[PDB]
Amino acid sequence: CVHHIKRRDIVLKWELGEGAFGKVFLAECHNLLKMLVAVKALKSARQDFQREAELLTMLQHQHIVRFFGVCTEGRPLLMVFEYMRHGDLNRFLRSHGPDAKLLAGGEDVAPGPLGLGQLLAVASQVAAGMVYLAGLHFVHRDLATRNCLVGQGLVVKIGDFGMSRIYSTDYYRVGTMLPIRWMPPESILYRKFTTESDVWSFGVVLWEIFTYGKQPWYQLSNTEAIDCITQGRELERPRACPPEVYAIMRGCWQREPQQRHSIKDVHARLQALAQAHHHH
Ligand SMILES: O=C(Nc1ccc(OC(F)(F)F)cc1)N(Cc1cccc(-c2nccs2)c1)C1CC1
Ligand SMILES: [Cl-]
């Protein structure tokens, strides 16, 4: 079922970044539809790549980054994805925040912070991707803005760099890299990962969106953040966050996993708020 792509049809442009087990390149792909694509090159490694390819071929949704296939005939092994021009959502939020004008290039279009409508549109799209994954009983385990991508026209989709571990500071070593600031108490304490720990992570993503990409618990060390989370401390309402949006975050952050609101209900509430603000 996995689509295969000839090595001749992939023209590497430049290396975007690299991690311990992979390198990501911007490339052009021929006879796929010239087309820009993001290519992951693998540094057992195989079989894990094969399971990954099968999984990415089955995950198909408007808010999941598009996977086009693999290149296995030759070395290294390649995975081909659509190119998301505006990069990862954490960097996107940080570059479209209150200090956007200071950071902007001279030619940037209408520099300034994203407005409420745009922030709800980002939030609703991430929630839609999570509704799809929950429907498949798929647990992401690392939902965070660094793992979402932004395309032209404020199109937001869920991904997973794997190599996120630029963002090494967002993970804590115990003893495996865990994104503790995005995790609920049961995941930090017992590594219990479920659709309910993903909804908790979505509440944290909502907080990152409304703080224009700040790191959750930024004032705290990893050990201090683990202690705050397990003690039940809640992140502060962001200045740009309306009370209705903070109530949605609180619904994702109920201590008992079974008490957390479903991602379908969270998505429905964000869509309703986005609809109510469209003309205002
Ligand atoms: O996000 C991924 N991979 C990935 C996707 C989906 C997925 O399914 C799940 F459900 F978990 F979401 C799992 C893993 N990337 C990053 C990625 C992809 C596409 C474009 C871009 C860029 N375009 C511009 C600057 S960077 C980057 C791969 C490492 C390549
Ligand atoms: Cl509330």
Image (spheres, rainbow, N blue to C red):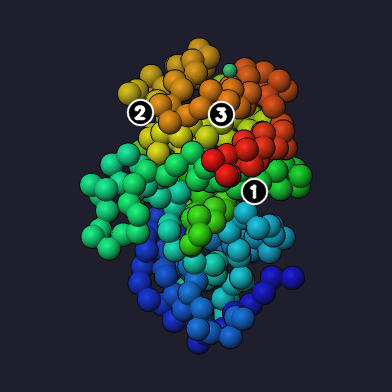
Q: Is mark 1 within 8 Å of ligand 1?
A: yes
Checking the image for residue 225, the label placed there is none
- In this rendering, the answer to whether 176 lies above or below 58 is above
Checking the image for residue 129, the label placed there is 1
- In this rendering, the answer to whether 211 lies above or below 228 is below
Count every numbered label the image shows and give the total. Answer: 3
Counting from the top left corner in percent of width and height, residue 133 is at: 69, 46
Secondary structure beneath label 1? helix
Packing grade of label 1 (10 A; few <14, some 14-19, many >=20) is many
Q: Amino acid at mark 1?
A: Gly
Q: Nearer the viewer, mark 2 or mark 1?
A: 1
Residue 87 in which image quadrant: bottom left
Checking the image for residue 218, the label placed there is 2
Task: Give yes or no for contact between labels 2 and 1 (Cβ–Cβ under 8 Å).
Answer: no
The mark nearer the N terminus, 2 or 1, is: 1
The answer to which of 72 and 162 lies nearer the viewer is 162
Q: Badge 3 is on which residue?
A: 245
Q: Amino acid at mark 3?
A: Val
Q: Amino acid at mark 2?
A: Tyr
Q: Is mark 2 within 8 Å of ligand 2?
A: no
Query: At x 49% / y 18%, what residue is drawn?
Result: 234
Counting from the top left corner in percent of width and height, residue 67 is at: 61, 65
Counting from the top left corner in percent of width and height, residue 53 is at: 64, 63
Query: At x 50% / y 45%, what residue is drawn?
Result: 118
